[PDB]
Each structure stands twice: as structure tokens, then as C-alpha cells.
Image (cartoon, rainbow, N blue to C red; front, side, top):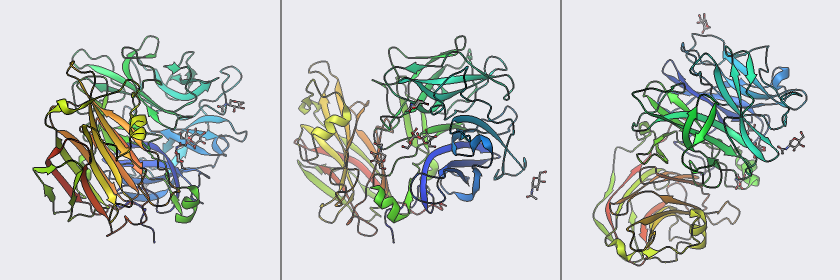
Amino acid sequence: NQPYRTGFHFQPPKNWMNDPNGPMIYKGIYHLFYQWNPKGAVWGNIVWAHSTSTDLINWDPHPPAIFPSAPFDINGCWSGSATILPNGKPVILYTGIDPKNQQVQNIAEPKNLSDPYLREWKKSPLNPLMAPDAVNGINASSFRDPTTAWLGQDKKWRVIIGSKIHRRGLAITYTSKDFLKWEKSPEPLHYDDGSGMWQCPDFFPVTRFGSNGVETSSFGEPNEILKHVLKISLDDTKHDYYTIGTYDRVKDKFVPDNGFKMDGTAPRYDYGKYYASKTFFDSAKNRRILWGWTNESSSVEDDVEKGWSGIQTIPRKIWLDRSGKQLIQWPVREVERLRTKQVKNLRNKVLKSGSRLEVYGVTAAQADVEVLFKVRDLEKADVIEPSWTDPQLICSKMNVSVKSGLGPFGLMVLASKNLEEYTSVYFRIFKARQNSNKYVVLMCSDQSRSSLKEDNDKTTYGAFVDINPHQPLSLRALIDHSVVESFGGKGRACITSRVYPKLAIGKSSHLFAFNYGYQSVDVLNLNAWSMNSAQIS
Ligand SMILES: OC[C@H]1O[C@@](CO)(O[C@H]2O[C@H](CO)[C@@H](O)[C@H](O)[C@H]2O)[C@@H](O)[C@@H]1O
Ligand SMILES: *[C@@H]1O[C@H](CO)[C@@H](O)[C@H](O)[C@H]1NC(C)=O
Ligand SMILES: *[C@@H]1O[C@H](CO)[C@@H](O)[C@H](O)[C@H]1NC(C)=O
Ligand SMILES: *[C@@H]1O[C@H](CO)[C@@H](O)[C@H](O)[C@H]1NC(C)=O
């Protein structure tokens, strides 16, 4: 009755969904809460719906845990997070709205401490632990989204909240004696002028040279080398920006790396439809999982008709790149279990100027794509014009049918029978200069013809990929009907989007490997795997 729902991602079986809340692991069992509306498909009566997992793919439902049932949140149960106590106990810090509509911070512990499901959450009476008042003085309507809490070189527990002072975005921190009495720190971990409110802030360390993530309370180790990443969801831009740096424990301030603010030149986790993103430390695999919400690119009139709004992007694994100034993301390996026992392959195939070879035997609407493009003679690449600095902007000013020396060439997913409607993520190579052997790799995700219904978020997203076009260029594509996640250079580039085709659905879907550019490129290899369904609820 509806071909726009995902088969292996995650979403409620009905109604609106928002921010990802309190992601963690306890007794080998992962947990996921989130902003959910039990009444309709439009933001409302938000509650902390629950679900659990053993492979971050299959989810078992559970009745809402944090919902309005006390003064301190009688008007709403906003986003929060869960900290792992130095004994294995998992609590929660969430923003509730009290009887006089003002963002207060409340804490919540579990009931049956032995229950591996933690379905019943107990909410302290001392709540709220933190609230905007006459002394702290802050926009009571702009003090929410508390992060996970990290100890320190002492007993002092630290955490930050997202606020704003006259357009001055920041992260208010509160030191805690023993996770009960919280003192309002007289200085934000950081802040940035210009950018509005700071939402869904997240603060966590990353080892420099290591794939597996680091704990949340790790401090100055003489053997291991740590770095820090503060990410915050912006308001007036609806994107996610992070930044890497150091953390002077003295002034409890965050110091980004060599000239890098949180807005202006700040990198995005995802250069497409991403939001409310948040991480969490996996004790079991020693990795850091990254959750992201991702709006609904369909008109609301649709969310009301289809009965649902909001999907959750596949948990990603992030970590610092070798260069040290960019996070590397790549979906959880355990998801490749939904891959059909079969295997669609294609190796050593030429892509003549403006050619395209179809990928046949595969659920074109629910698969895992993956290509390795090879570019010969990089010299044929064009030299970028000055102005072209914003990735997104270039991909929007130069659609798919506009040729380039090296490009455009990538994938066409959920493509229609004869291309009346298709999606096209691809690459374009240019020279940074002319003789200073340095190239720029453009990753574009065109949405202009993603569907036939003019009423959809057709905005195209753009991004740059820090890879060396000397070797082959990678590009993966998770395919799941309405949602498509793009990955370039092994995650180095993550552009996700939402499509709603009228002809490209179910068994009527097609895939396509193209190259409509001048110079012809080669397909060193390409594997498309059909993807079975995941038990979501
Ligand atoms: O409880 C809502 C929950 O969502 C967030 C996500 O960033 O709120 C933002 O998005 C809303 C929908 O566009 C806006 O109305 C709201 O003003 C904005 O902050 C979280 O901040 C919040 O916890
Ligand atoms: C509730 O928690 C208690 C912890 O003492 C546990 O003994 C009990 O099994 C739980 N409830 C049940 C029976 O599921
Ligand atoms: C800040 O607070 C004032 C009064 O509480 C409110 O009118 C204003 O909208 C707030 N600014 C925003 C949008 O964060
Ligand atoms: C959020 O989703 C809406 C549709 O509900 C879309 O139009 C918009 O581009 C997305 N982000 C914003 C507010 O720009």
C-alpha cells in the first residue's frame, strides 16, 4: 500500500519520528530511544519510544520510556542522552518542559536493574537538576539537548547543553559533584558568533591513529594520543557541523585545530539530509556508532497521507582520518548480513563518453551498491574556476547533462524504466591549480529528476572528497526505496537523500552505472548485492 517505507533501515511502523535519544549498550544489549508522536505523522506529543537490538539492524519494540508524567516535563519529553556510570549503570539526561513552558534538564534511572531491556524508567523527584533562572539567566526557550556526561581529571562530572545568547551559539556546561548537584560553569566549552542556536551538541574523544573508538572519559594518556570532536546541530541551517581539536582541562574549554570555527568552514557529518546526529561508545566491539535522523523530503500533505514521517539512518562508525583533520564514517559491517546470498558482479568494463551499463539481477530498490572507478590520464581533468568553492553550489549549477573532462560519472539508483526519473550520485575531477599536482574530487548527488511528482525536496547536495584521483575512486550506495545513502572514498564523503519515485518502485526498479562526461573512465570492479529485509518495529 506504500512503497516508500524502508526494508532494512529503521522507523516507526506508524507516525512521526524525530531525534535519536540515549543510544548505548548494556549487558550486550543495545538501546535506541527517540522522539516519536503516538498520535500523528506531524511533530507532536513527542515521547521517548523504545526499541532494542543485538546487531544494530534488527529491532524489537517496547512501550515509551520517557513521556510527560510529572511537573518537570508535563509539556514535553525532549532529546537527551545516556551516560555509562563507572560501574556499568546507565542513566539519562533529557530536557523536559515544565508547566510554564521553559526548557529544564531532568535525569532518569532504570527500574528493574537486572532487566536486560530497561523498559521501565524511573524519574527522580529532585528533577529538574538544571534550569534557566534569574541568576544563570538564559533564554528558557533555548536550553536543551544535554550530551553524555564525562568525568574528568577529578570527580567533577562535566556535560554541556545547547543554548544561545542573542545569536551567539554556545554549549553551557555544568560541573557535578556526584551526578546530583550540578554547578553552572561560568564559561561555555566553546561558542561561535553568527550561527544561531546550538542544538544536539555532542562531545567525545578520538585516538589519532586507531580505527576503534575511544571511551567518553579518557584523559591525557602518555602512551595513547587523543583528540576531541565537538559536534552540534545548527538551527537556522538544519545541518550538522563538527570540529576537531584539544581540550584544556584547565579552562574546561574546547580548542579546535589550527583555525577552524564551528560555522564557516566546519565539516558536516553528512552533506545532504542529515540532522539531530549523535554518537555513543560500543563497549563490546570497541567502536563508536553514529546515529542520524534525516528529515522527510516529501511534503507534509504526504506524511499525513502515508501515515508516517522520519527514518533513522544506518548506524555509522566514525573516527579520525590519518591526515587528522576530517572524520571517517562507514556503516556498520554487521549490516552486510542483509546481503542476498547471490552476488551481482561486473569487472573491467569500459564507460565510453556518455555511456551507461545496467546492473541486472538485483533488487534495484533495496540493495548495496559499490564501485571502484579508475581514471586514466588525470591531465585531461579540467581546472576549477575560482568562484567554485561550495560543493553543493557547484553540483547545483552544473546538473548531470553538463559535460566535464573527468566527469560526470557515478551511479543511477531507483532509476525508472527509460530514465524519466532517476537519481544520480557521481564524481567530477578537476585540477586544484595547473602544475601543483593537486586535484579536487567532487561528489554530487543530483535529485532534480529523482521523481516525477514535482512536490518533493528535489534539492541537490554537494561535497568534496579528500582522496587521490591517482588511485581508483570508491563510491558505495545503500539502496532502500525512499532513502539512499551515498559514500565516497570509504566514507570520506557522506551525502544522503530522500527520493519518492512514481515509476521506480518495488520490482519495477533499475540501477545504472554511467559516465556522460567527455573522457571515458573504466570500471575496475562493481558489486551490487540485493538486500533482504530487517525486522524493524
Ligand atoms: O523536541 C524537539 C527536538 O528536536 C530538535 C531537533 O534539533 O528541535 C529542532 O527542530 C524542530 C523542528 O524543526 C524546531 O521546531 C526546533 O525549534 C529545533 O530546535 C531538538 O532541539 C529538540 O530536542
Ligand atoms: C524486576 O526486577 C527484579 C530485580 O530484583 C527482578 O528480580 C525481576 O525478575 C524483574 N521482574 C520480572 C519478574 O521480570
Ligand atoms: C529568546 O527568548 C525570548 C524570550 O524568552 C523569545 O521571545 C525568543 O524567541 C527567544 N529566541 C530564540 C528564538 O531562541
Ligand atoms: C526538513 O524537512 C522538510 C520537509 O518536512 C524539508 O523541506 C527541509 O528542506 C528539511 N530541512 C529544512 C528545514 O530545510
